[PDB]
Image (cartoon, rainbow over all chains, first blue to last red; front, side):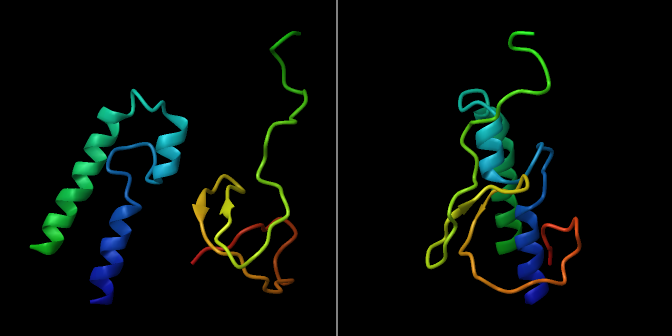
Length: 55
Length: 55
């Protein structure tokens, strides 16, 4: 159970093809208008990770 | 060399203020951004160049 929770929390630190994993970094170095399509893939990757974990 | 060079002033806002506990004060030091409460713990065993510590 601890390993599953740690692996799930480690999924948040994953890059998922992006430059970084921190939300403040991606929302600060990138512009608030051109980063929507780039953050969409990260948000759906995290959502599908949640779906796989709950399954 | 107007608006081009290496050495110049750096009077912008930097995260170097009077830090204190009892509240998760925002920290943006050493290229790391996060949210957490600071706690005064004595640590003298650090190296001359060591600044942080990881888990």
